[PDB]
Image (cartoon, coloured by chain):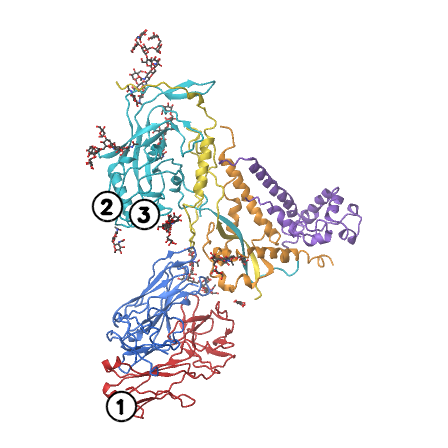
Chain colours: A purple, B orange, C red, D yellow, E cyan, F blue
Amino acid sequence: LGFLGAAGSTMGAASMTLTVQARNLLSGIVQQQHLLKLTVWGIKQLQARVLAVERYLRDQQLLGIWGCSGKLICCTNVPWNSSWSNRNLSEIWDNMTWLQWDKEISNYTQIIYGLLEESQNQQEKNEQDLLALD
Amino acid sequence: LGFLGAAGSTMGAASMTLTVQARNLLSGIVQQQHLLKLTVWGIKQLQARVLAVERYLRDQQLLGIWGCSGKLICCTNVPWNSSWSNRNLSEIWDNMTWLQWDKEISNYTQIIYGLLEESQNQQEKNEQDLLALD
Amino acid sequence: SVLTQSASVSGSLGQSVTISCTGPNSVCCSHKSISWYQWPPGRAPTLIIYEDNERAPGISPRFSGYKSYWSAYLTISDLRPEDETTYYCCSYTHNSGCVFGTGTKVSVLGQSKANPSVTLFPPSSEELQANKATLVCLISDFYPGAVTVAWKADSSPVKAGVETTTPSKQSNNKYAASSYLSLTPEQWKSHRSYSCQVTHEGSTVEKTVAPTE
Amino acid sequence: ENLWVTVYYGVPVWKDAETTLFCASDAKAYETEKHNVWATHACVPTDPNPQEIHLENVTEEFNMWKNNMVEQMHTDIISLWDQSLKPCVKLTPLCVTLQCTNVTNN
Amino acid sequence: TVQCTHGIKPVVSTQLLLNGSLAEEEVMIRSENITNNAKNILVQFNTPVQINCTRPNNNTRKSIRIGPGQAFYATGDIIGDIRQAHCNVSKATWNETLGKVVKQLRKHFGNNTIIRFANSSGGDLEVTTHSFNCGGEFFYCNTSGLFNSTWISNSNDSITLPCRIKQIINMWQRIGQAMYAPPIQGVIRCVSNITGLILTRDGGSTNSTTETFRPGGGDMRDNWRSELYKYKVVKIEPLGVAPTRCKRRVVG
Amino acid sequence: EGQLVQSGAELKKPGASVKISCKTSGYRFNFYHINWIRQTAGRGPEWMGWISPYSGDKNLAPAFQDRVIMTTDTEVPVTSFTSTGAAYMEIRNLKFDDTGTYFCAKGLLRDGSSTWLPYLWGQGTLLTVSSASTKGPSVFPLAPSSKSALGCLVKDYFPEPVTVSWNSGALTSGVHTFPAVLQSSGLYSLSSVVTVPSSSLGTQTYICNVNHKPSNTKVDKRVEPK
Ligand SMILES: *[C@@H]1O[C@H](CO[C@@H]2O[C@@H](C)[C@@H](O)[C@@H](O)[C@@H]2O)[C@@H](O[C@@H]2O[C@H](CO)[C@@H](O[C@@H]3O[C@H](CO[C@H]4O[C@H](CO)[C@@H](O)[C@H](O)[C@@H]4O[C@@H]4O[C@H](CO)[C@@H](O[C@@H]5O[C@H](CO)[C@H](O)[C@H](O)[C@H]5O)[C@H](O)[C@H]4NC(C)=O)[C@@H](O)[C@H](O[C@H]4O[C@H](CO)[C@@H](O)[C@H](O)[C@@H]4O)[C@@H]3O)[C@H](O)[C@H]2NC(C)=O)[C@H](O)[C@H]1NC(C)=O
Ligand SMILES: *[C@@H]1O[C@H](CO[C@@H]2O[C@@H](C)[C@@H](O)[C@@H](O)[C@@H]2O)[C@@H](O[C@@H]2O[C@H](CO)[C@@H](O[C@@H]3O[C@H](CO[C@H]4O[C@H](CO[C@H]5O[C@H](CO)[C@@H](O)[C@H](O)[C@@H]5O)[C@@H](O)[C@H](O)[C@@H]4O)[C@@H](O)[C@H](O[C@H]4O[C@H](CO)[C@@H](O)[C@H](O)[C@@H]4O[C@@H]4O[C@H](CO)[C@@H](O)[C@H](O)[C@H]4NC(C)=O)[C@@H]3O)[C@H](O)[C@H]2NC(C)=O)[C@H](O)[C@H]1NC(C)=O
Ligand SMILES: *[C@@H]1O[C@H](CO)[C@@H](O[C@@H]2O[C@H](CO)[C@@H](O[C@@H]3O[C@H](CO[C@H]4O[C@H](CO[C@H]5O[C@H](CO)[C@@H](O)[C@H](O)[C@@H]5O)[C@@H](O)[C@H](O)[C@@H]4O)[C@@H](O)[C@H](O[C@H]4O[C@H](CO)[C@@H](O)[C@H](O[C@H]5O[C@H](CO)[C@@H](O)[C@H](O)[C@@H]5O)[C@@H]4O)[C@@H]3O)[C@H](O)[C@H]2NC(C)=O)[C@H](O)[C@H]1NC(C)=O
Ligand SMILES: *[C@@H]1O[C@H](CO)[C@@H](O[C@@H]2O[C@H](CO)[C@@H](O[C@@H]3O[C@H](CO[C@H]4O[C@H](CO[C@H]5O[C@H](CO)[C@@H](O)[C@H](O)[C@@H]5O)[C@@H](O)[C@H](O[C@H]5O[C@H](CO)[C@@H](O)[C@H](O)[C@@H]5O)[C@@H]4O)[C@@H](O)[C@H](O[C@H]4O[C@H](CO)[C@@H](O)[C@H](O)[C@@H]4O)[C@@H]3O)[C@H](O)[C@H]2NC(C)=O)[C@H](O)[C@H]1NC(C)=O
Ligand SMILES: *[C@@H]1O[C@H](CO)[C@@H](O[C@@H]2O[C@H](CO)[C@@H](O[C@@H]3O[C@H](CO[C@H]4O[C@H](CO[C@H]5O[C@H](CO)[C@@H](O)[C@H](O)[C@@H]5O)[C@@H](O)[C@H](O)[C@@H]4O)[C@@H](O)[C@H](O[C@H]4O[C@H](CO)[C@@H](O)[C@H](O)[C@@H]4O)[C@@H]3O)[C@H](O)[C@H]2NC(C)=O)[C@H](O)[C@H]1NC(C)=O
Ligand SMILES: *[C@@H]1O[C@H](CO[C@@H]2O[C@@H](C)[C@@H](O)[C@@H](O)[C@@H]2O)[C@@H](O[C@@H]2O[C@H](CO)[C@@H](O[C@@H]3O[C@H](CO[C@H]4O[C@H](CO)[C@@H](O)[C@H](O)[C@@H]4O)[C@@H](O)[C@H](O)[C@@H]3O)[C@H](O)[C@H]2NC(C)=O)[C@H](O)[C@H]1NC(C)=O
Ligand SMILES: *[C@@H]1O[C@H](CO)[C@@H](O[C@@H]2O[C@H](CO)[C@@H](O[C@@H]3O[C@H](CO)[C@@H](O)[C@H](O)[C@@H]3O)[C@H](O)[C@H]2NC(C)=O)[C@H](O)[C@H]1NC(C)=O
Ligand SMILES: *[C@@H]1O[C@H](CO)[C@@H](O[C@@H]2O[C@H](CO)[C@@H](O)[C@H](O)[C@H]2NC(C)=O)[C@H](O)[C@H]1NC(C)=O
Ligand SMILES: *[C@@H]1O[C@H](CO)[C@@H](O)[C@H](O)[C@H]1NC(C)=O
Ligand SMILES: *[C@@H]1O[C@H](CO)[C@@H](O)[C@H](O)[C@H]1NC(C)=O
Ligand SMILES: *[C@@H]1O[C@H](CO)[C@@H](O)[C@H](O)[C@H]1NC(C)=O
C-alpha cells in the first residue's frame, strides 16, 4: 500500500486509498537533485522534469473545470448513460480492477469528459445568475 | 509589508498579511523576459524557471489533497497532539516568529503531513457515501 | 495602597484556599484585567496567573480563578507543602503598568509538627579579645512558625540581654531563627554558668552548656 | 485541550541553501558598441525600479567566506570567458621558429 | 530582502581591487580567520584613491591573412617615440589611506607591534604585480613602490609605478587554452577608482612583535568577495502549520 | 526562558543619586519591555515604570515621573534569537522611605492584550538609604560546644548582606545557611550553618571566608581547636 498497493485489488479497495497514488506521482523521482553542465544526463533530466509537470497540469486542468479543484473524489451531477456499461451496482465494484475498467470505457471515455464540463460547470456556475443576489 | 514585511514580526501579525508573501513568489523574478541563444545565461534562466514552478507545484499539490485548493488558511479537522508542543494558546502566537516555529516542528513536521491527508480528505471525501444521495 | 487583599488565610494539605480582592472604580476589578504573583519575602518572586484565568506556562493547572464585577480571587487547589508564602496581585489595563495589592501571607496548616535539631553555639577564644558578650543558637524545621525568647543567667531571665530577632522561612520550606546577646564582659565574668531556654511544645530535653568551660 | 491544527500557505520561513542565479543588466552599449564578453549578446534586462524591502526584528546570520554566491560567480565568469573565445581566430600556425633582433635604440 | 543585487562589475584585478563598493565607516577589515596569518585578508577603502594608468606607445594594426579568412593582428613599427607604461597614484591621498588601515588593524592586531610593509615577496610576476585588463591590453604595474612606507605607534607630487604590457595570457591559472591580445591601435588610458586591497601572510613569527601583510592575490574568487560579503540566498518555505481551536464542517 | 541578573549592592546617602543596572541574557532584548518595582519596610511592593528598548516610548509612574527617569541603550545580537543587553535607571531624590530591595523583570509578552507586566525576575538589588556611615564587619569563629552542624560567626556589621561564607567553594551541596539579625545598637550580625557528617579535625579543613563591600575582605579565619 506504499504505492499502487491496490493495483490488482478491487476498485472499491483501491478507492479506499487513492490518496497515496496521487501524492507520489508529481513529487516523485528525486528531480530536485570539468566545469560544464551540458551533459547528456542533464538534458534528459530537464525534459523528464518538464513532462512531470506538464502531465500533472494536463490532468489538474480537467478537475478545475469540474468543481474538483481540491477534492480527490467529486460526485458529479451528470447522469450515467446505459450504453456505456450494462453492469449493476455491485457487479463492477466487487469484481473488476481499475485496469479492466480503464479498457472498458477507453472507447467512449472522451464522450464522458465533454459532457462533464457542461452540466457540472458550464451550467452550474451559470445557475447562480438568479440565485446569487435576489 | 511589501514582501516579508512581517518576517520578524509575531506569528499573529504575519498571519494578518500572508497573501502578499504568496503572491510574489510564483510570479517573481521577471522571468518572462551573434544569432545563437545557447548562452550560459539562458540555460541558467531556464532551469531557474523550472524549479520556480516545480517548487510551487510541489507545495500546491499538498493543499489540493487537504481541501485547500483555493484558500490561504484552512482549519483542518486533525486534532493536535500534545507531544508536538506544550505551549498554550497565547504562549506561541504572541511570542514566536514563524522562523522560530519552523525549527520547533521541523523534527515532526512530516508526521503532521501524513495525518492531514487521512482525516481531512481520505475520510472526509469518503463520508459522503451515505450522505450524498439517500 | 488602593488595592485590597484577603489578609491572612489558612488552609490544609490536599485542599483548597481562596484569596479575594476588590477595589474602587478608579483601579477596581470591573473591566480592568488583573494578575497574581508569588512573593517569598526577601527572596525572588514568581508569576502565576495572567490577565484573568489563563495560567502561566509551567505553573501547574492546580491554580483556578475568575473575575466578577468587583471580586477577584485565586483558588489554589491541591495544596502542596511548598505554597506556604505570601502572595500578591496587581490590576492593569492594556497600556498601563501594574497596581499591586497589600499582601496575603498564606500559611498552610495540616502539616506535621516537626521537632527541630537544636544546638547552642558558645563563644570561643576570639570573642574574649574584643570582650563583646554574645551567644547564639540554631533552630531548623521547628514548625509551626512560633517563637519564644528566653534565657537563664543566674537561674533567672535576663531583662537587658534578650535580643529578639526576625524569624525566617527556611529554603527547605520550613523555618529558621537565631537569638543574639548584647552585654558587657564584666557581666559575663560575674555570672559563670549559663542555661538555654527554648519553650518548645513537648518534652523538657533542652541542651544546656556553660560559657567559662 | 480541544485544539485543532490549521494550515497556512504564505508563511515567511526559510532555510540556508543555494541554487542557480542569472544576469540582469539594462540597455548599456548595444549599437555604439556590442559583442561584450560579459553581458554576452543578450541578458535579462533589469527593471529601473529597485526591488528592496527593509526587514525588521530579524537577525539572520550571514556568511561570506562560506557563501556560495561567489562560487557560482567564479564559475560563471570562467564558462563565459571560454564561450566568447571559442568562435574566434585560432593562432596555431604562429608557432614557428622565430628569428628576432632587438628594436632600434640607436 | 532584495530580489536583484546592486551594480556588480567583474573587475579582474590583482592585489588591488578597483571600482568596488563600500558604505562608510572605518576602512573595513575582513578575514576568514584572523588568528591564522596564512589566510588571505580582504580590505575595503572608506574612500577610493583615484589612480590613472596608461601606455604611451602609439601602435599600428598590422593585419596578415593566415589561411582563408582569418587575420593575425600584430604590432607594426611604433610611431612617435617609445616610452614605458606607468600608473600614477596620488602620493598625498595614498599616505592617508595607509594610515587609516594601520589604525583599524591596530585594535585588531594587538596595537603594540611594528608595521613592516614590503613588496610582494615570492610569487610570480603576474600574481605579485597589479595585473589587470584595461583598454584591451593587459597591464602589470609594479606594486613594490606603494608599500614601502612604514608607520607605527604615533601641481602636487604623485608616486608612479613602472608597468609592462603582455599580449599572451591565460588568467586565473587556467592551463587549458591561452589567448593572444591584439594590440589596441591608438591611445590608452585607464583612470579607475581603487577601493580594495588584498594582503597575505607575514612569515611564521613566533610571538615577539613586528609584522604586517604584504600584497598577494593568489586566488581570483576572493576578488568577487569584496562585493558579495553581505549577500546570502535562502530557500523560502511557504508552508507552515500551527494549531488553533478551529475546525471546518463536520461531514462533507 | 531568558535569565535576567541585576547589579546589586549599591548604597549611598539620602540626598544622593545612584543608578542600578541589569544584565540580560538568553532572550531578544529588542521588544521585551523592562520595568521596575520596589518593596519598602511597608508591606506592599509597588510598581515603577516600564521602558521599551525599541522606540523608547515609556509611561512611568506619575508619582516618580518628576524625579526618577530611566533610559536603556541598544543590544548586541548573539544569534538570530538570543541576545544580551543592559538597562539602567537613575533616581534623583530619595529618603529613608525609599530604602529597601529593588527588582527588575522581563516584559511578559510581545503583543497587545498585556505586555507591560513582568515575567522573568532577577536576583535583585537591595538599597539602604540609612545615613549612618559604612563599617567593616568583624569575624569570629563560633566553635561547637559538645565536640570535646558547623559554621562561622559575624558580629557588628553596618549594612546590607555579606552573602557567601565558605572557603574555596568546596561544598555547595548540603550547606544550610541563616539570615541576618537587628541589634539593639542597630549594628547587624549573622551566622551560617553547614551540614556535614561528624569526623575528625586533623583530617579535614575548617576554614571559611566571607566577602564584603562596605570594606574589602582578606582574611578567612578558621576555628579554634577547643
Ligand atoms: C517588531 O517591530 C515592530 C514595529 O513594527 C512597526 O509597524 C508599524 C505599525 C509602524 O509603527 C512601524 O513604525 C514599526 O516598524 C514592533 O512592534 C511594536 O511592538 C510593541 C510591543 O508589542 C507594541 O508596543 C505597545 O503595544 C501596546 C498594546 O497595544 C494595544 O492595542 C493593540 C491593538 O488594538 C492590542 O492588540 C493590544 O493588546 C493592546 O490593547 C488594546 O488597546 C486598545 C487601545 O486602548 C484597546 O482599544 C479600545 O477598544 C475599545 C473597544 O473595544 C474602545 O474603542 C477604546 O476607545 C479603545 O481604546 C483594546 O481594547 C485593547 N485590547 C486589545 C485589542 O488587545 C500599546 O498599548 C502601546 O501603545 C503605545 O505606542 C502606540 C504606538 O505609537 C501609541 O499610539 C500609544 O499611545 C502608546 O504610546 C504600544 O504600541 C507596539 O505597538 C508595536 N508596534 C508599533 C506601533 O511600534 C515590535 O516590538 C518588534 N518586535 C516584535 C514583537 O516582533
Ligand atoms: C622592424 O623590422 C622590420 C622588418 O625589416 C626586415 O628586415 C629588413 C632588412 C628588410 O629586408 C625588410 O624587408 C624585412 O621585413 C622593418 O621594416 C623594414 O625596415 C627596413 C629598414 O631598412 C626597410 O628597408 C628599406 O626599404 C627601402 C624600400 O624597399 C622597399 O621596397 C623594396 C622594393 O622596392 C624597390 O623599388 C623601390 C621604389 O619603388 C625602392 O625604393 C626600393 O629600394 C626597391 O628598389 C623591397 O624589396 C623592400 O623589402 C621594401 O619593401 C629601401 O630603399 C631601403 O634600402 C636602402 O636604404 C637603406 C637606408 O634607408 C640602406 O640601409 C640600404 O642598404 C639600402 O641601400 C641600397 O638601396 C638600393 C636601392 O635600389 C638597393 O638596391 C641596395 O640593395 C641597397 N643596399 C643594400 C645592399 O642594402 C631599406 O632596405 C623596409 O622597407 C621595412 N619593411 C618593408 C616595408 O619592407 C622595421 O623598420 C623594423 N623596425 C623599425 C621601426 O626599425
Ligand atoms: C572601472 O571604471 C572605470 C570608469 O572610468 C573604467 O575605466 C574607463 O572608463 C571610461 C569612461 O569613459 C571608458 O572610456 C570609454 O572609452 C571608449 C574607447 O573606445 C574608443 O575606441 C573604440 C575602438 O577604436 C576605434 O576607434 C579609434 C578612435 O577612437 C581608432 O583609433 C581605432 O582604430 C578604432 O577604429 C571606438 O569604437 C570608440 O568609438 C572609441 O573611439 C570610448 O568609446 C568611450 O566613449 C565615450 O567617451 C568618448 C571620449 O570622451 C566620447 O567621444 C564618446 O562620445 C560619443 O561618440 C563616440 C565617437 O563616435 C562614440 O564612440 C561613443 O559611443 C559616443 O557615441 C563617449 O562619451 C569612453 O571614452 C573606458 O573604456 C573604461 N575602461 C578603461 C580603458 O579603463 C574601468 O575600465 C573600470 N575597471 C577596469 C580597470 O576595468
Ligand atoms: C618593482 O620595482 C621595485 C623598486 O624597488 C623593484 O625592487 C628592486 O629589487 C631589486 C632586486 O631585489 C633591487 O636590485 C638591486 O639592489 C641593489 C642594492 O643596493 C646595494 O648597493 C647599495 C648602494 O645603492 C644605493 O641605492 C640603494 C637603493 O637600491 C640604497 O639603498 C643605498 O643606500 C644606496 O644609496 C648599498 O648602499 C646597499 O646596502 C648598503 O646600504 C644600505 C642602505 O643604507 C644598508 O642598509 C646596508 O646595510 C648596506 O650598508 C646594497 O649593497 C643595487 O645595488 C642594485 O643595482 C644598483 O646599481 C646598478 C648599477 O649602477 C643600478 O643600475 C641600479 O639601478 C642600482 O642603483 C639593484 O638595484 C633593487 O634595488 C630594487 N629597487 C630598485 C629598482 O632600486 C622590483 O624588483 C620591481 N619588480 C619587478 C617586477 O621587477
Ligand atoms: C584559524 O585556523 C587556524 C589553523 O591553524 C586555527 O589555528 C589554531 O592555532 C593554534 C595555535 O596554538 C593551534 O594549536 C595547536 O595546534 C597543534 C597542531 O598539531 C600539530 O602537531 C600534531 C602532533 O605533532 C607533533 O608535534 C606536537 C606539537 O605540539 C606534539 O604535541 C606531538 O606530540 C607531536 O610530536 C599533529 O597531529 C597535527 O597534525 C599538527 O601537525 C596541536 O598539536 C596543539 O594541540 C595542543 O593543544 C590542544 C588543544 O588545547 C590539546 O588538546 C593538545 O593536547 C595539545 O596540548 C594545538 O592545538 C591549533 O591546532 C590551530 N588549529 C588547527 C585547526 O590546527 C585558528 O584557531 C583558526 N581561527 C581562529 C579560531 O582564530
Ligand atoms: C530534533 O531531533 C534531533 C534528533 O532527534 C531524532 O529525530 C526525532 C524526530 C526523534 O525521532 C528522535 O528520536 C531522533 O533521535 C535532535 O538532535 C539532537 O541534537 C543534540 C545536539 O547536537 C544531540 O546531542 C549530542 O550529545 C552527545 C553526547 O551524549 C551525552 O549524553 C549521552 C546520554 O546520556 C551519554 O551517553 C554521552 O556520554 C554524553 O554524556 C554529543 O556527543 C553530540 O555531539 C551531541 O551534542 C542529540 O543526540 C540529538 N538527538 C538525538 C536523540 O540523537 C534535536 O535537538 C531536535 N530538535 C528539537 C528542536 O527538538
Ligand atoms: C599616433 O600616430 C599616428 C600616425 O602617425 C598619428 O596620426 C597622425 O597625426 C598627425 C597630426 O598632425 C596627422 O597630421 C599630418 O598629416 C600630414 C599628411 O599625412 C603629414 O604630412 C603631417 O606631417 C602630419 O602627420 C597625420 O595625418 C596623422 N596620421 C598619419 C598617417 O601620420 C597620431 O597623431 C599619433 N598619436 C596621436 C593619437 O596623436
Ligand atoms: C592602543 O592601546 C592603548 C592602550 O593599550 C589604547 O588606549 C586605551 O587603553 C585602555 C587601557 O588599556 C583601554 O581600556 C582602551 O580600550 C584603549 N582605547 C581604546 C578605545 O581602545 C589605544 O586606544 C589603542 N589604540 C587606538 C588608537 O585605538
Ligand atoms: C496549557 O498547557 C497545559 C500543559 O502544559 C495543558 O494541560 C492546558 O490544557 C493548556 N491550556 C489550555 C488553554 O488548555
Ligand atoms: C638584445 O637583448 C638581449 C636580451 O637578453 C641581449 O641578450 C642581447 O645581447 C641584446 N643584443 C644587442 C646587440 O643589443
Ligand atoms: C588622474 O588624472 C586626472 C585628470 O584630471 C587628474 O586630475 C588626477 O590628479 C590624476 N591622478 C593621478 C594621481 O594619476
Write down the residue under mark 1.
Answer: C191
Given contact means CB atoms under 8 Å apart, are the residues at marks 1 and 3 in contact?
no
Query: Which of the two marks, 1 or 3, is nearer to us in this view?
Result: 1
Residue F95: quadrant of the picture: bottom left
Would residue E175 be seen by someone viewing this image from the given angle?
yes
Write down the residue under mark 3.
Answer: E25
Q: Using the numbered discs, state the Cα–Cα distance from disc 1 to disc 2 in whole angstroms.
A: 79 Å
Same chain for the residues at labels 1 and 3, yes or no? Answer: no
Mark 1, Cα crowd under 10 Å, few <14 / some 14-19 / many 20+, is few
Chain letter behind tag 1: C
Disc 3 marks which amino acid? Answer: Glu
Residue C70 on image: x %, y %? 47, 76
Write down the residue under mark 2.
Answer: E152
Q: Which sits in the foreground, B106 or F50?
A: B106
Mark 3, Cα crowd under 10 Å, few <14 / some 14-19 / many 20+, is few
Image point (26%, 85%), residue name: C183
Q: Quadrant of the C terminus of chain D?
A: top left
